[PDB]
Length: 29
Length: 265
Ligand SMILES: Nc1ncnc2c1ncn2[C@@H]1O[C@H](COP(=O)(O)OP(=O)(O)O)[C@@H](O)[C@H]1O
Ligand SMILES: [Mg+2]
Ligand SMILES: [Mg+2]
Ligand SMILES: [Mg+2]
Image (cartoon, rainbow over the protein chains, first blue to last red):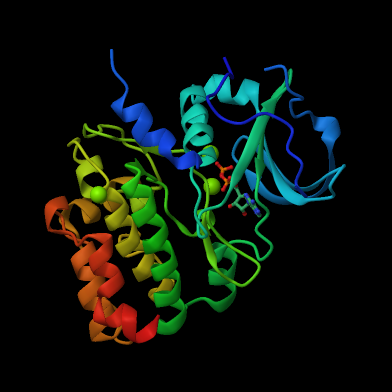
């Protein structure tokens, strides 16, 4: 499986992400 | 996703920029905007045989969410039938590794400047609780202005709470706690920095030996000496980073304030 929780959408290179770490650390179950 | 996803047909591929273990990294240009970047290829069959599929996922997820001036940008990724592709920010001046073969040694100004960029980069990383774990010349690239950029998050990990047990990295850069089968944390990158600083000034890692067993022995004992041209300040710093006890090694904030660093950086 090569399904990662990361970007894979085409981006227009001519035209705040790091909270991902703490938000994933704080999530519950 | 209902959005347009990356595809190989989106980039014009140029020359190879480097040779990776699971494939080459090629220069590339996105066709619509003509934005120049780097394309890291990984052959899936190689990755499967090696069983490093979970580490690829950590490289991508961790690097793609990091944003800093001295850390190589991971814009995105896509895979196809036989391989996986990472869309990386292009590092125009190559690797510190190559610059080190050319100059053989780095003087103090150059060494402190690099340590400073890397220390700032690692500090941001730790604030996010990420441990790089594969800091070495071949994973350090130079940007448009000769600024260091950390790359290759292959052996990285997100360690919010717990310690780790993985032995990973490069032989000459392995921390004592890993070799000895003990648990580790973000302090392993502080050891790597000491190993790296020494190599920059001397031209070779401090525990280099003729065999694997001998190198393990020297790291575990923290057995090394300095040639005579290494100044007192550099010795005080490398000696502090190369403490057998992880707790005794300086914080990155201390390295950044180290007298030798501020005098030469
Ligand atoms: N963005 C990039 N720009 C320029 N060269 C790169 C880039 N990414 C990798 N390289 C070159 O490719 C080599 C190997 O790829 P790297 O991603 O560092 O790890 P791996 O060995 O796991 O493939 C580097 O040592 C460097 O010479
Ligand atoms: Mg911290
Ligand atoms: Mg590498
Ligand atoms: Mg790798």
